[PDB]
Figure (cartoon, helix red, strand yellow):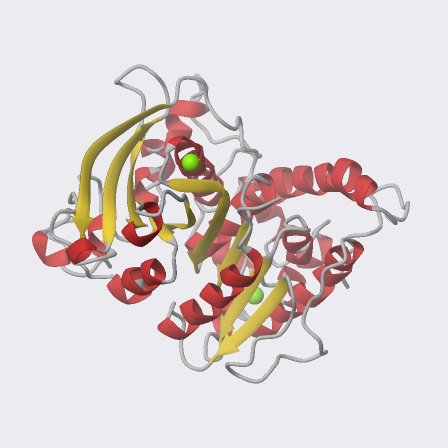
Length: 397
Ligand SMILES: [Mg+2]
Ligand SMILES: [Mg+2]
């Protein structure tokens, strides 16, 4: 049984956009922070420094300008940093125009999103499952290893820049990774035990996405008011939490984000709260473990995280065979979030059951399910590019 997003914590009905934006949204953001992801301890830190390390105006055979940027989270050269890779379509900037952007984290390093041999190899810890890794270190053989999730050339040909950062720059995806992370520097309390409401990897990954947006605001080649933040699976959990917390993001795409992302936790289908916390104890707050095999006690569910994107366009998508993510749970979260989008005059999927494969449904709140297993395919990206065409042609007032 789901909590109503349009009934406030004190029982009062939310009938208007101002009550939603200025009372209900903060209420919900604090519940997710305390009980699920942990508290984001600060937004933009003082002293952000942006250093363009490489700049090639004829990348991808002339189709793109490629930028690599060190985004340091403080002015001292000893503060932590992340490495941002950016491809911008030369066709747009040759017209004296700023390109809209797709921004998303990657799983195995910037050098894996494209075979482009001029990308810096990540100098960070790489997980064991990464293709062609030599003892947790990037290798030349890993180049383009994950390019099937990154149709860079097609995205650029449709008029969008592509920005990415390796999630492991922010928090290595391993159970001890928070100790080697922004979190270890940022909320570096004198103590050692992680506090019960301290953020984990998803919170730290999300914060990195907002810091990448800070960089895009300074880059004259891109329009930072037209940024679609996207992610696949665990990095899609991060894209949703980033897009919910930071309403600068123009559009939000959740590709098969599953448990603790778009899927309802109270459905108890596929991956559950207990299973995700037991396998990935660093992803959520320790407080989220209160709900292991007790999802009935959750004071929110993930439809309210989706509602936190409203009125900005939100795309939630599933893969038919990806039962672990609970595709029907992701769809029903979209349906339970729709009344908030409707409050703002937007439309969600028509229907009470999962649509047929490869038949997207909904207006600014959109869903599709595609055939096959978990992944981020050319078919997913085709639907996202049409979505962005419709809801990200926003360079006019
Ligand atoms: Mg800009
Ligand atoms: Mg589930």
